[PDB]
Image (cartoon, rainbow, N blue to C red):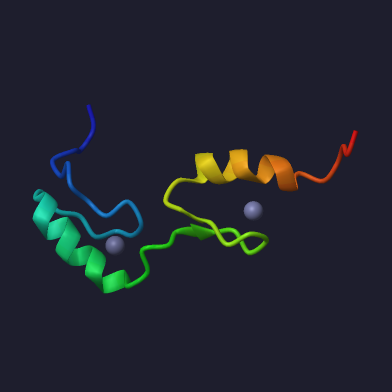
Amino acid sequence: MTHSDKPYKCDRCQASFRYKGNLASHKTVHTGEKPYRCNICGAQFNRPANLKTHTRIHSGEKPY
Ligand SMILES: [Zn+2]
Ligand SMILES: [Zn+2]
């Protein structure tokens, strides 16, 4: 058993909410819809998975 009654909570800080609209309202507080940005190229990503795959090219440790 575990505590869980806020399906719509900010997965960035302690803040939590039971409504999706409220979450969006709270998101305005952070002011920065750019979690990850590639300085090398300039691409913006909302997920680290894509960034990890993107780093694949930048992965300098085996040129050939
Ligand atoms: Zn937050
Ligand atoms: Zn890049």
Specify whether 63 is left or right of 25: right
Q: Which residue corresponds to the image point at 66% horizontal and 45% vertical from the top-left?
A: 55
Q: Quadrant of the C terminus?
A: top right
Query: In the depicted view, which residue is nearer to us: 63 or 52?
Result: 63
Residue 8 x %, y % = 18, 47
Q: Position of residue 12 (x, y in %)?
A: 36, 57
Q: What residue is rendered at 45% in x and 46% in y? A: 47
Q: Is residue 5 left or right of residue 53?
A: left
Q: Quadrant of residue 59?
A: top right
Estimate the x, y position of residue 62 in percent, counting from the top left: 87, 37
> Farthest top residue?
1
Quadrant including the N terminus: top left
Answer left or right for 18 relative to 64. Answer: left
Q: Is residue 30 above or below residue 42?
A: below
Query: Going by the image, does 24 lie left or right of 35?
Result: left
Q: Nearer the viewer, residue 61 or 42?
A: 42
Relative height, residue 41 to residue 5 (above, below): below
**Taking 35 as reference, is 30 above or below it?**
below
Q: Nearer the viewer, residue 48 or 37?
A: 37
The mark tally for this picture is 0
Q: Residue at x 22, y 51 (%)?
A: 9
**What residue appears at the point 56 percent right and 46 percent down from the top-left corner?**
51
